[PDB]
Image (cartoon, rainbow, N blue to C red):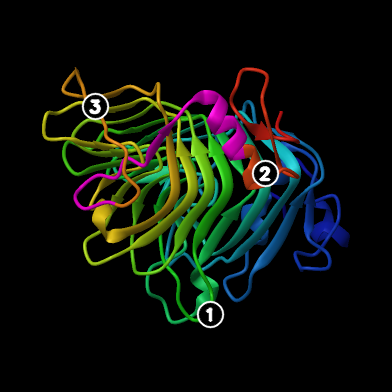
Amino acid sequence: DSYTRVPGDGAGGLFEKGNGTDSKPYMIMNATQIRNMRSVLKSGMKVYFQLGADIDMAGIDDWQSLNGSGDFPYEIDFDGDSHVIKNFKCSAGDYPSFFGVLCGDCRNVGFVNASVSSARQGIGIITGYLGLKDKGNGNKTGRIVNCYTTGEVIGSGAAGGIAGVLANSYDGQESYIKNCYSNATVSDRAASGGKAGGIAGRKVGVGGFIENCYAYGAVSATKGGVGGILGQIDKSCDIAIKNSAAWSNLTGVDASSTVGRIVGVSASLGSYENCYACESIVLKVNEKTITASDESSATGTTFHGVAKSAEELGNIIVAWNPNLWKKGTNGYPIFQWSE
């Protein structure tokens, strides 16, 4: 029985149609239906969802993340089908975000004017964790592909425009973020050990990557690491970041902060290719402007990539996938289907 006002196919009318399988995904046409997702999750198998329209979540106060609690038992396949979810808000429950912990796939969705906040946990708009670390079952990895976010993220211990924490790769599957952008303001307000990134706050485990991503929302931490793409790589962990660009202003408030155009902390643990930053971004630590030097690998804490002009970056980003990306009228690339 539904907890919402909507309402047999579509789980008896909770959705427009479908049964949560690959061939019959639960089809979501409005925000009341999107609020029924939690009711049809299954601890024993991945459940499939698809958007059939843009979804405006204005006036929705009762979201808690789909898979942020317990042992994170719910695997999810989500296809936005090139639609947007507007005015999504979450500031309560475990891992405030859309998914909480994403085990499975999210593709082809934009979040417009989202607002997610936590005083206690590391978060992003789409998910808190993308994948789980070092599980025995590859179905616990997670991928976000062809997605974007705008709005605001406030976390504590990690903050990313897309995900709080990216996990790793094992058992024949990989965790990654690919062909995504964000314009969200991203802030890690932890008193110490902040991990703020334009795309992801933190990376855990060995294996996993970020590819064909850029960000342009302001990224900051009260006291910690700030990166245009990634805040922190954990000790004894790694990442690859390839064909990506930083286009955000980056601010570490405390003097002990580290700011990297691409990666903010333990950047030498990563492997990089074709990483760029707009020449006009402003980097600050303790209110003092910092210069960054061009580099294509990291030898120390931060990784800055190579500076490019706005015009150059527009060329570069669209070339990542000309069927997906387009130049925006204000210089910032977006998707062909972006609102």
Give coordinates of residue 25: x percent, y percent: 78, 61
Residue sitting at 35 percent across and 69 percent down?
206
Q: Which mark is residue 172?
A: 1
Of pointers 1 and 3, the one earlier in the residue sequence: 1
Instruction: Of the two numbered discs 3 and 2 on the same chain, state the one appearing first in sequence.
Output: 2
Please name which of the two marks, 1 or 3, marks the residue nearer to the observer: 3
Label 2 element class = strand
Residue found farthest to the left: 256
- The boundaries of the magenta stretch are 298-317
Q: CA distance from mark 1 to mark 2?
A: 25 Å
Q: Which element is circle 1 on?
A: loop
- Residue that numbered label 2 is attached to: 109
Left or right, 72 with respect to 311, comes to: left
Mark 1 vs 2, N-terminal side: 2
Image quadrant assignment for residue 21: bottom right
| CA distance separating discs 3 and 2 | 36 Å
> Which mark is on residue 291?
3
| Secondary-structure class at tag 3 | loop
